[PDB]
Amino acid sequence: GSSGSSGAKDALLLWCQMKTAGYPNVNVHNFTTSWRDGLAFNAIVHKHRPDLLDFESLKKCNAHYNLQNAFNLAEKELGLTKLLDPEDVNVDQPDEKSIITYVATYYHYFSKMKALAVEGKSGPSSG
């Protein structure tokens, strides 16, 4: 029982889906059993910076690591605040609300850069 396309966390869900699409293994269908493994996160970055990590080297078995690595790499390179952990998220049915918030940063952040925008931020600076 479902028609058309309804939902609030769609704009984002679609974003990750489009990017992740590049890879077959990587698939963003939901916001719970999609980031539990880790690849998902290791798929968004690699896309922007294939240097940071080597998806090819990564494996679709280990999560605890694939998670911490992604959270770290970004928490260091990009400079995002680790809101979640590679152990907290890794679960049968994690809190989609606790994840959507994190992944939301990847979109906003990257978006800030040279890209389409309307009535947004003037991107401040300091240094």
Image (cartoon, helix red, strand yellow):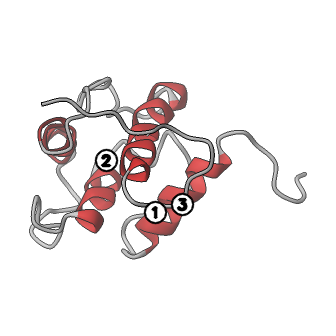
Query: What secondary structure is marked by label 1?
Result: loop
Give how far across and how far down residue 117 sits, in percent. Answer: 56, 53
Query: What secondary structure is marked by label 2?
Result: loop
Give the CA separation, mark 2 to mark 3.
31 Å
Which residue matches tag 1?
27
Which residue matches tag 3?
116
Q: Residue at horizontal 48%, vertical 57%?
A: 16
Give the image quarter of residue 26. bottom left
Task: Give the mark nearest the N terminus, 2 or 1.
Answer: 1
Cβ–Cβ under 8 Å for marks 3 and 1: no
Q: Quadrant of the C terminus?
A: top left
Marking on residue 106: none
Type of amino acid at the residue the image marks with label 1: Asn
Q: Residue at horizontal 46%, vertical 61%?
A: 115
Give the CA separation, mark 3 to mark 1.
25 Å
Type of amino acid at the residue the image marks with label 3: Leu
Nearer to us: label 3 or label 1:
3
Q: Residue at horizontal 36%, vertical 42%?
A: 36
Identify which residue, 76 or 24, lies in the foreground.
76
Indicate whether 56 appears above or below 116.
below
- Classed neighbour count for the residue bearing mark 1: other residues with Cα under 10 Å, few (<14), some (14–19), many (≥20): some
Q: Residue at horizontal 88%, vertical 53%?
A: 2
Query: What secondary structure is marked by label 3?
Result: loop
Which residue matches tag 2?
37
| Residue 108 seen in the figure | yes
Indicate whether 46 appears above or below 41.
below
Type of amino acid at the residue the image marks with label 2: Asp
Q: Horizontally, is 74 left or right of 26 in the view?
A: left
Nearer to us: label 2 or label 3:
3
Task: Give the mark nearest the N terminus, 3 or 1.
Answer: 1
Give how far across and how far down residue 20 sits, in percent. Answer: 42, 65
